[PDB]
Length: 191
Length: 157
Image 1 (cartoon, rainbow over the protein chains, first blue to last red):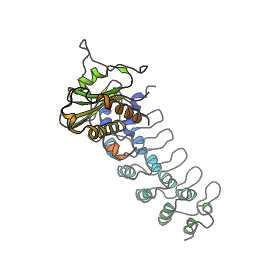
Image 2: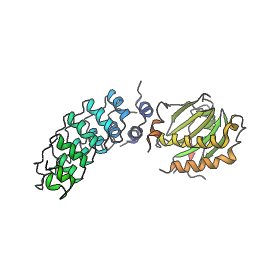
Image 3: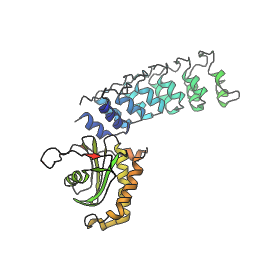
Image 4: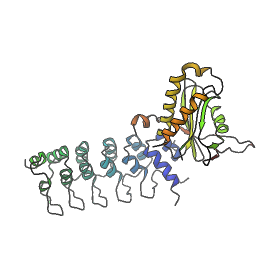
């Protein structure tokens, strides 16, 4: 029930404060690189969420767990993807964070990046092995979501990398029958 | 409850201006902090109880503040860089030879306005400031020789 120390640490992580993190964890009170706020937020989550790429190698160096699940069963990759943090995503993928993990809404890192319009993350993730056609609990794919949210550049990139256009989400729609009639997006979904 | 409790500008152990918004042994603590600061340019944070003490020393002038331990260092250092910029612009080299509290009737209200402003709720400049500002513990001595704690009363002023 006393999370006050944990909160000190995560506020420092969140502010990108490496010397504070170092003091609080005593590098080179029961705190550790993998403790959790009440949420399940570990430092690695927080760092990812706030895009603190300079912290990540260090946390990982001291044993942070990149597959740690918060209360949404989200891993830190999800958050960095939700927020569009390139270097964080890169750093984690390069430290072997797994790209195909689903949280309770069935979403993936790729799907969050696409949903959020973060095109600069799509190729990177595909390279590290994200399944381009995985779907969330609504049966939407990265491509469904990019289309719904109208992120043209994302749509472009997913089609270029061969994303299926025949997946039916749970209301029997496909990427195509989610676009505008006469959208530039629609044009793209034909070629 | 503004999370920045106190601020001063000093040279050496000589305070030139100060401002607190509530009651506490700020000067007792502050005077023992000043006496530990090397006069060469440097920046540091001390962690003490539930508070943090932060300063910047530059061109011999110390820009210092005390805050609750849940106010982000970035926000603190930005407060200080802002106070400093004003101090430097307004007083220039005068601060090198100023006597005690010489700036206090003019500047404590600037300190007050900034403390308020910065205490009421982003950029990357501000978080990269923090690079290599160590966090340390500090040995502070009370009247009867025991460990001195910062003891304030938020009820006040």
